[PDB]
Amino acid sequence: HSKNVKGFLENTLKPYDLHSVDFKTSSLQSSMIITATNGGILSYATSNKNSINEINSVNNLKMMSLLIKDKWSEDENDTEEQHSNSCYPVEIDSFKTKIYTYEMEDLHTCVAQIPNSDLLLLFIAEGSFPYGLLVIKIERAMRELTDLFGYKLG
Amino acid sequence: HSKNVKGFLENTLKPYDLHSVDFKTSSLQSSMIITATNGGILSYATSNNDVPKNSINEINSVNNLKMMSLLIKDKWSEDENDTEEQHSNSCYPVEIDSFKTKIYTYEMEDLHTCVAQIPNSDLLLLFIAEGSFPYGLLVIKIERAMRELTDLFGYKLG
């Protein structure tokens, strides 16, 4: 806190330690790599007890992945209005991609093409996980995936 | 690091350790409250890193801030009353308590900027930062900052 509006604005200029920032949730629900061509899951992890729920959970991820890939591909051919909440152009080692965000019912999702590839990296989180954090997260995580830059399904 | 793609994905599920996330830039260049009607600056602060705090410099930088505030307000206004023709890089509807607003981000030459209407008011909160200040961080920051400005919710000019 501060005395007045001027002092508040001066305080906003100080270095913003993401340290002092509390989040309701900062963990993902699910994370996967899917094809940019058809939204098929090539690899996934989830946080979310029995056999049918393991099966069901993969089925639900497949449906979600398909929906998200459709919105991503529509947004990429920018001849219509954007489904996405955000489109941030980014560079990892001079490889370019774009970070999109999609609301899916109560969930926050974030997706980016692995640069030059036929693959998307997709994060799925509860609605309490801020989009700003997802965007930071996905850009950093993408740096780990240089092996897959340019990956072609062929 | 990790062993394979599966392990990489599993690692992304863990609580995002903020204590490890380094940024090139996490300080704003400038911060202001401007009118949603005309983009007129009502209060501002700017960092003193470039030139000495003197006279000509002060006059010049305020003039620049006024020009930028106007351009950004115009972009915001246009975005607020349409669907498909968005200038902004993002638009996040947020709720503070039961009040609603929207966080917009704009590329301004090499600068990253972030703006949100102070809920139910004639005022906008505007952040200006260098291009190395990630938009995701600006969005987090302005939502949190907006929580401190309840005194100004419902503020009307006149």
Image: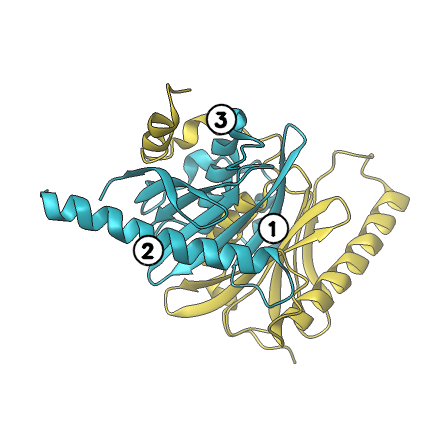
Chain colours: A cyan, B yellow
Q: Look at mark 3 in the image and give the residue it sits on.
A: A144
Q: Position of residue B111 (x, y in %)?
A: 72, 45
The quadrant of the rendering that contains the C terminus of chain B is: bottom right
Residue situated furthest left in the rendering: A50
Instruction: Indicate the amino acid at tag 3.
Output: Glu
The reply to the same-chain question for discs 2 and 1 is yes
Q: Nearer the viewer, mark 1 or mark 3?
A: 3
Say above or below: B123 vs A49. Answer: below
What is the C-alpha distance between the residues marked 1 and 3? Answer: 37 Å
The spot of residue B83 in percent (x, y) is: 60, 73
- Return the disc, 2 or 3, that comes first in the chain's sequence: 2
Q: Residue at coordinates 66% horizontally, 51% vertically from top-left?
A: B113
Dot 2: element: helix
Note whether residue B59 is visible: yes
Element assignment for label 3: helix
Residue B114: give its label: none
- Chain under callout 3: A
The residue tagged 2 is: A63
Q: CA distance from mark 2 to mark 3?
A: 26 Å
Label 1 in the same subunit as label 3: yes
Name the amino acid type tagged 1. Answer: Leu
Tell me the element at label 1.
helix
Of the image marks 2 and 1, the number of the one nearer the N terminus: 1
Please name the residue that numbered disc 1 is placed on: A9
Q: Quarter of the image for the N terminus of chain B: give it.
A: top left
Query: Which residue lies at the image location 73% right of the left edge and 68% below the top edge?
Result: B74
Q: Residues within 10 Å of mark 3 (few under 14, many from 20)?
A: some
